Image (tube, coloured by chain):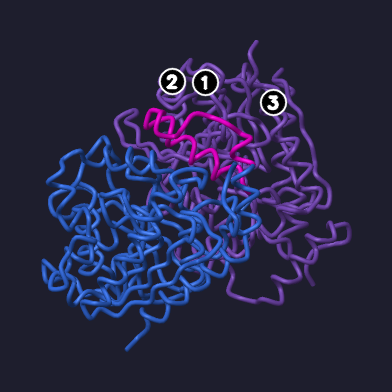
Chain colours: A blue, B purple
Amino acid sequence: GSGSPGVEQHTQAFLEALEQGGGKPLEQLSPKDARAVLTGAQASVKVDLSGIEVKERTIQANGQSIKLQVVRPANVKGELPVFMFFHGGGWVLGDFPTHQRLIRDLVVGSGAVAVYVDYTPSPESHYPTAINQAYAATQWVAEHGKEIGVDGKRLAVAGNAVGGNMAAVVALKAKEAGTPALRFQLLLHPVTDASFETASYKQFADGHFLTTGMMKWFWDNYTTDAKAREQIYASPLRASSEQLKGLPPALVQTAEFDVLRDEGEAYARKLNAAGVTVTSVRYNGMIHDYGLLNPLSQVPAVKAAMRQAGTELKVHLQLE
Amino acid sequence: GSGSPGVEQHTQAFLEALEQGGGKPLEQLSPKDARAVLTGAQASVKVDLSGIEVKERTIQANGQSIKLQVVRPANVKGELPVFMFFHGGGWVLGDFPTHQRLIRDLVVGSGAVAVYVDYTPSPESHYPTAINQAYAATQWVAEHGKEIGVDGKRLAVAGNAVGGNMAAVVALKAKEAGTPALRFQLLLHPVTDASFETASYKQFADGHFLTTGMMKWFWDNYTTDAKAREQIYASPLRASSEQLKGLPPALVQTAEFDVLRDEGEAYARKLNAAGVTVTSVRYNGMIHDYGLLNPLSQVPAVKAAMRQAGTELKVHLQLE
């Protein structure tokens, strides 16, 4: 009673193992206990984190202190291009160490520096606190890149799930502010709409790791303000073609067996209809967050997806 | 022209590979460039860092801000015993990420929490700044342990090389202050004396990774004050039996092919002569910092040494 026909074999086994593991629904836990689920699960897998050097940095931007983790390809001299990395976890969960293997794969694969932004979790904060932090840090990197060994003029945004939401919305905030210039947005199965009635939402409501109950809980912790949810900085799928016009080139990866699949692909279509350059790719057989979850990190399709994400970062961040 | 007869086979190969790699003597580099040597070398090796959860914490202790990295066994509930971890690197080099694999091995092997203390490097600071930070953080953990999920009443100190110096000296500062109580000191090939005329110093002056030139440079960056060097908080080997009396039980590991071997073993003898409980173990075939260097981390003797260090931590930190 886990998964579906066509789920990739290792992923299916992972889903079945979780089912036998039992446990309360994530959304019935305290934020503290939910956070520990991800922490514990990520830590229980031997993973390759080599080839990077990590350094913390606190910045002052748009009137607040923001913590960064700068992840640089190891043994490389000189200024490097750079991508902001916005972590997923449904706004409630996630942090740098839970996401470090994913970030590492993107850094080693791209040859570019990642700047993880430690945005304030929900429900400790609500919309739009984190995205304002996300944007503030992005502008800071553009202006002050030399201080952390990067070329801030060659700048992308990237994230998984709500992190993909965050990357897409930071690109919109950058358009609104007229700064900074962005080369590329990498959206790994993004949340793009505060609604729950797409065909994929109905089909994969449960049994496929990310449940409908989880997503609704995530959104509720983020903000219960219906008017806020209707804003394009919360639900970018609601943007018009005019509002999307001029956004940077995008790679959108979606997972076949993901409640978020349809809104992610729909967002890619809206970008294309607005004249934005988009590569929209559905990874068949995959579940949500296949790039994040360390138990899936050696699944061949996941390795392929990660090679592509790193390559496309590289391609869009090179010297013109 | 690298190593010696009796150097363990993988270690010998490592030494020979380094020799073919060439490069300037470490002590002819800027501190920034020397630091990058360790960073780059550690990052170029795939290593297992699983089974731990890492969280940063800044504390206020004895009138200053001190950064900690708290490394906890993953998926474990409740208060755990705890060891301070003081990193090596000759006071000039080293930090948390360079030492993370070593710390991880100690944490996973012991079941105890590590508290890495980010002391100020030399020459940015000199003696006794770092050891005062080291001690301040140790007392803080003893008083405030519950805030980071540990039983501060079950507290050890641990470190490699100058970190071993630091652990030994923090135990002496704790005796001097009458607080906190310590269960155990783990000294991995400690620096114990600002002198360079032991038999091991003469025999292994070069060709065995840690050179005499390096040690002298390390000490010079730490402090060129001859009077400072004569203090027991810099050169604990100079302590009298009375001064050593009452120190906590010790495990001292030394490496056979290490300039520091003789002063480390001599310090173990002084502890024993003062009535302190000591286990003093020479790991034959090994070079300095065998537990730190990631290229050596799968050498069987190194794995054995790491199993022992973790076990002895565990044994001394249990409930009485």
Q: Amino acid at mark 1?
A: Glu
The crowd level at tag 1 (other Cα within 10 Å; few <14, some 14-19, many 20+) is some
Q: Which mark is residue B271?
A: 3
Above or below residue B151? Residue A36 is: below
> Magenta part mainly helix, strand or loop?
helix
Residue A200 vs residue B53, the one in the foreground:
A200
Foreground residue among A233 and B288: A233
**Residue A21 colored in magenta in the image:** yes
Residue under mark 2: which chain is it in? B
- Label 2 Cα crowd, 10 Å radius (few <14 / some 14-19 / many 20+): some
Q: Position of residue A254 (x, y in %)?
A: 43, 63
Residue B124 against residue B21 in the figure, above or below: above
Residue pointed to by mark 1: B79
Q: Which residue is mark 2?
A: B146
Q: Between marks 2 and 3, how big is the CA–CA gap?
A: 32 Å
Q: Position of residue B90 (x, y in %)?
A: 55, 52
Question: Which residues fall within the magenta stretch?
Answer: A17-45
